[PDB]
Image (cartoon, rainbow over all chains, first blue to last red; front, top):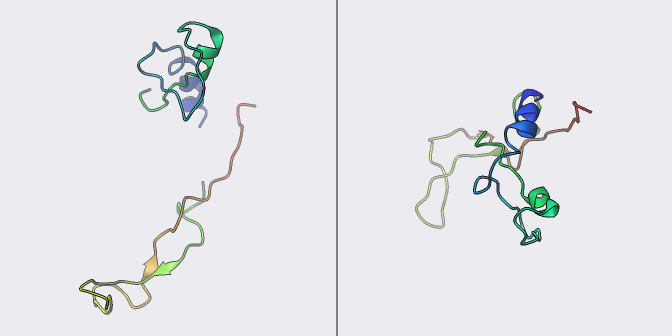
Length: 48
Length: 49
């Protein structure tokens, strides 16, 4: 339960897009590189 | 997580199917056995904090 939190915080996040997914009706700013866009874009913990 | 992966859950019997009847298969037990209605009763930690 601690090794998976380590791989999610470094090697699941900081991953280029078309892998991360946006959840139910969270408004992303359409700027592809602003901070709130990389924030609300949430990484999958199953592909890594 | 709990021990057996399932908390106190309900006993469901064994039921065959032809029509409205839905009775008496003799393919499962009379009482049957518990089959976990719902989700697993978990509890939560923040162990890195």
